[PDB]
Image (cartoon, coloured by chain):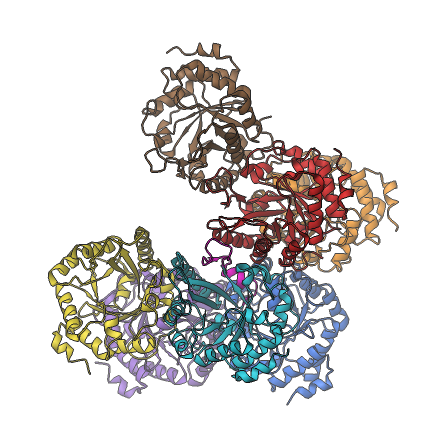
Chain colours: A cyan, B red, C blue, D orange, E purple, F brown, G yellow
């Protein structure tokens, strides 16, 4: 079993709604860009992007409390709901600054299945975030709320945010502080990323990154990441900014849940 | 209708006192300049100005707490009361700094129908305000208190505070964090502003701006803003600093509630 | 439909896990007898029973905190979890006395989808329970936790606990105080029960009762109850004390979710 | 001038939604019988009854938190919402026992304009209720929530619950403890009731009682009560159990708001 | 293992100090009689009784906080500490009345490894204790403190406190409410007690009772109890009031931890 | 009249102890210089200065908590007590920095009749003080404690702290944030100060300032200030550092309470 | 006996699980490097390292809460658990910055036997840490939780972090503020370190430091440190990054618990 070591009935129950019973993997679609980047392609009509993506395979979605109270359909099949707790914007005089904008209690009373926090390890006064992650991890432990920690090496003195050692360190940091799952950048090659995965006691979900050149490159990255040990993927733009949202997620699901090869999943992108 | 998603009995009930049942639009008159600018034309005799626009069919007013305890008419059209929670002054060594000076509880025990907060996205340590908006959004959700978030792109590195992308981003930011209604600057043209409106999940009320030159210009801006998708307007100086407060508000109400044109509107200004 | 007028996101989300999307009905299996009656046939091996009732249709189970942390399938058909908050025993000098033994917070941090309380209207100092139901309804409203109120007319001066008037009163009492769903005894005939259903603003789930003499009689009662307006059934002993737990629940599900008749239902009972 | 000694901005604002600006009187329709008596004629379809009486011109209704989530309309004319805090039933082993079942905070976050409590002065351990009224009055004072205290002389040693001295005492008791408005039985004659009114510092609203037999008798009682000094009436059954709900309330409103005599009034009831 | 279903790191860690790693059984020596019966043979010199019993093989000792602050050896053999939370005396006008006299927090800050509560199911107002057990179970769950619930069928209408059905019910009651371990009377025969054990989801520890006649009868009862399914024994008087405390406990440990037989057990008693 | 729109029983009652019933004006003597300047002429023997300033007419003094426990008498004429909440010293690396050093609760439990706070609008991080004034205003509103806000335009970029526009702004700021009374510098001429008075919704008390070299000059300023609209004066040094404390206050009282002319007044200074 | 003065029952009980009864010394293995340095040799497979170090005779391990949730076993000699409360990373823009990331309460509900905090005396704003240590010392005193303060002289103006005077000062600082045990660097020679030990009222545990060149040098340092007065050692890398973890710890235990000599102890390390 994947989480067969966590002493928390509540966490298990809720983790069951974000991971696939059979594959023990997960396909999460982050849709929180509205806060940091503003209205972007694909995130204007949330209910559309959400319902589709669900129809395409996704296990759960990532959203800010302000947007949940809206994009609720309860129509098509159901996907897990992860509420983001961090805030920060590009237009801010310090883009890397992240602050807690939502409480764990708020998320649970909204019916969320998990909460996520973003930590830019290496940014100015990032230690304040260490404390945040640490304290939030505790309230999460109490409420039986699964916590996803998105750890990224970003700051003034960091040129390569994908450096293997830094990413491995950041991921471990999140597990050490109490996160149940860790989100982070793929290092570029199967071997270095495998180090990130083996160096972190908690399941690691890989980030998709900016919109890729070809669906083959993108789908290949995910394939490699999985073969390295990832417990799933958390793709945003590469999915909802695609021409065929339903199809592209189908591909991702094929690769992640069915171990299907790239050449195959690629035939799902029906125009 | 308007708030089709809002799932909070208390908020609905109170929103009914700030929006027009028939038009589903709103005319709000901000009268909080006393804190940031001091005693200015039109705000010396509050009870006069209140009932002035209130008589002009204004739905609600926006006062600070230390004035409402004074500004209590008892006559003239019962208008909604919105209590401002933010504070900051021009005489401060940092004019863009906004701080919470009133709690949501205080506002509700004063019989307010809604509360408003000001966020200068892009200013120094603006992330502190993100947290404020986020946390206040939650207490508002709890007390069933409608929250109006006035989002403005202002800061050291922002030359054009009316830039379409920045304004659209700021507006979205407010909705994402839990605001029920968003106040913001009109971008200048119907098309760009329409992007602001469509990019924000919550109703958007447009700001009037400092006193303009000719009324036609002013009434035209409001007309364009409405045709772009605004759910109403929040005009301050352009109304209470006018020669005919009652008439100018009548004009605004004509345009906003009855969809009249500029020519028609002006006909209500007796001077 | 069933729930349109519940303006609370958390409750909706959780109610989706106890009601059938298509039929808008529910089959609940109470397994809390351990507290009031002790170890009885069918409740010795909980994981077996809960599993049996699960891989056979039930959309949820009712247990006490100290049993959830025990019998947890985790491998099979996912059923909803309802945590009981009331306590009382037959061996007590006052069997009708019910007390709160578990808090709503405990239930939510265990991943429960709803909580239930038992109120013996008419028993000694039953007003204490009115307050309990009232206060608990509030904390439930806050946490977005669906509340099932099991209302029963029981006490010294009540000969017929199935009297139509009393039952209708008790059901209404529960809804008036804030319950989202009401559990109660079937009055005996379709017409009187229809009065209970129409007199109560909230969905009414009918109780199965102690062992009926035959499966046809039992299945007929459920059939009549549904035709009267019940939103589902909450059967305990009649199901887990049956010779074919999986089959008998199949029958109940057939009648409740598929409006199937009884001859077609009786067939489900694999004997 | 009705409320002068009220120095509670919040209370004033909210009282404006339950009293008529011009007549300074009020017509309240209690619809809380569901808790104490069960489903009765007129209270089965709440949304129907609420609309009709509101069309009648009635200023406000009195419900229980359970029903509010079942009486929102946004259909026709809006009426004030008073949330009842007390609970007790006829089926209880002690019908005169009243307990707090809802908090003042709950009521305000639901958008209520006032709260009411029932006190059976003279019943067993009624002193517990004195404390309740006393403490609730304080929380009401804090939240700016108008409090209606329904004071009744009921108990083992009280034969005549309409006795002038007892009723006058009970009314005074409510005002002394902090209630803003007092509900009570009409003593039978204009002179004795005038004593109740003059002996109580707070406005007194009279109760309708059960169905007197003929329109005239009922409307006469209200007429006499008003002439005695009542600040309005709180009629339940006599109105919603009538054949012409809209008309009968029209009559009551005529007498209470327009000082019309019974002859003119009855002209409103289309029978 | 014994606690396979226990998901709680803190409870596991502490349970390791009261149970034998190899046998997964436990020998507890209750020394709380001081409160209910006063100074009795064997409990006058606590530190003495505590090390001889610890020399023999005791795994834990039960004591009221006031005794704990005294009998600390720091030499001998380290045993688990269980702090009793209940209180009641024989000299009381109601001996069966038990009240919480110590909080869970007090126990944990004293370094206790577990807490115990006594519940006389069937006594006057025993429902008050149901609530106590329920609420205490929750705080125990929070602090990761193992809870031992001593359930006994005692009251006015109970002639046989050792009745199989009653004892099985009482035991189940404790597990249902959240206890981790249950203390109770041996029913008399291996078969009936086996029903108690199988009807209770939590490990069951058997009570020794009053000094039965010989070391053979006593040791036989323990032998039978173990063969029935007991997870250990909690013997008080039969051990510390014995002539050879160290030896008699040795015997008990032999039977409980090594499955030995009464014969090769008596060999422990140094006459 | 004066305290007209104010709706707070507690505030009214206490304001009656700092204002003269007949003139509706007030003479306050600040004696808090000990904190910011150290022991200065006149403040060494507090009880002396406080008995003198009392006899001369004063209606209330102003001290820090640690001095009230000194200037208490009973032997003489009673005066109001105002407890200062702000702290800051000249010897500090930032003299304009003011911090809350005493809570409102402390003041009320000392029998204070009002509290005061100092705000240097325009100083470094003065927004922190805005929040302080704002929050304190609320606790004051709750305890029915009159709040005097001493608003001064002081900071790096302010050359003229007596500038009419700045002072009028600062005064308005205090009222807007919830102060009941405002303390501030006299602008120099009757006309500009009249603007400060009319631009501020709350009564304005004028500061005496540094001891000017003529009594006529001093008494003239007070005379002009009163004729401009001041509700009283708050003179420190000009009074207690005078040769005839009793006489000089007599003069001030003559001018402020009896509308004397600067001539009859001077006939109070015997010295 | 060691902790003779300590008058804390809870602390004593727990200290018994980290110190050896006979030698009154302790061998602690810090495994918290994951947070500050990332995944390093020896810390990838925690359960492995932990049960091997445990097998070697170490008393307690020390890790962050996030990691305790994984590496736990129900076999082998169970060692003490110390939960680290401080956080900080090498990748941070300020490596010497330490922040509280875990609360004392969290540690005790996880079954910890002690908590540790890291204080870099001399670093930027280190006074913030003084407060942390101080306040945490109090909560520890309350919960009966042993506190280990790791005091190190590190900062901009400190060239030699092993300077005798600085280390002695840092150690005393920890004891003065309430720590029960102090961790610190060995000064280099037996005489200077003896000053550190005698200048600190609390037992001092020495740090191992970086992986030494040879086993003899390392084991010699420990030998000297013990002969100077150390109450034990806290070795990290030198142990778990060794080729024979079980053997090297055996050596350390030999030297620390048996006073054996380096060479006899070196006879425990196998190739």
Side of G51 relative to B82 (left or right) = left
* Outermost residue to the bottom: C271
Could you say which quadrant of the image residue B262 lies in?
top right
Residue pictured at 25% horizontal, 58% vertical: G151
In percent of width and height, residue C66 lies at 48, 72
Residue E56 is covered by the magenta coloring: no
Between E76 and C54, the one lying in front of the other is C54
Between G82 and D68, the one lying in front of the other is G82
Between B142 and E177, the one lying in front of the other is B142
Residue G250 visible, this angle: yes
Side of B137 relative to E39 (left or right) = right
Quadrant containing the N terminus of chain C is bottom right
Could you say which quadrant of the image residue E245 lies in?
bottom left
Residue D97 visible, this angle: no
Magenta segment, which residues?
A87-112
Between C41 and F236, the one lying in front of the other is F236
Quadrant containing the C terminus of chain C is bottom right
Magenta stretch mostly in which secondary structure? loop
In percent of width and height, residue E25 lies at 35, 79
In percent of width and height, residue B75 lies at 70, 35
Residue A90 is covered by the magenta coloring: yes
């Amino acid at each position: 079993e994947l989480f067969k070591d966590i002493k928390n009935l509540g966490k298990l129950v809720r983790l069951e709604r974000i991971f696939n019973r059979e594959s023990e993997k997960t396909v999460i679609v982050p849709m929180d860009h509205g806060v940091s980047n503003g209205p972007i392609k694909g995130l204007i009509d949330i209910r559309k992007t959400v319902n589709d993506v669900a129809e395409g395979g996704a296990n759960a979605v990532l959203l800010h409390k302000g947007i949940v109270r809206h994009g609720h359909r309860g129509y098509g099949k159901d996907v897990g709901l992860i509420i983001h707790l961090s805030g920060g914007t590009a237009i801010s005089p310090n883009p890397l600054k992240k602050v807690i904008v939502t409480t764990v209690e708020e998320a649970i009373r909204m019916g969320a299945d998990a909460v996520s926090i973003h930590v830019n390890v290496g940014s100015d006064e990032d230690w304040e975030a260490y404390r945040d992650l640490g304290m939030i991890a505790e309230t999460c432990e109490y409420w039986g709320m699964p916590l996803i920690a998105m750890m990224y090496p970003r700051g003034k003195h960091i040129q390569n945010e994908r450096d293997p050692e830094l990413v491995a360190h950041a991921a471990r940091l999140g597990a050490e502080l109490g996160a149940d799952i860790v989100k982070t950048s793929y290092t570029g090659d199967i071997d270095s990323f495998r180090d990130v995965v083996k160096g972190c006691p908690a399941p690691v979900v890989v980030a998709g990154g900016p919109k890729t050149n070809t669906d083959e490159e993108f789908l290949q990255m995910i394939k490699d990441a999985m073969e390295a040990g990832a417990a799933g993927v958390a793709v945003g733009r590469n999915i909802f900014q695609h021409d065929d949202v339903v199809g592209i997620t189908r591909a991702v699901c094929k690769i992640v849940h069915e171990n299907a090869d790239v050449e195959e999943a690629l035939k799902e992108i029906r125009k």
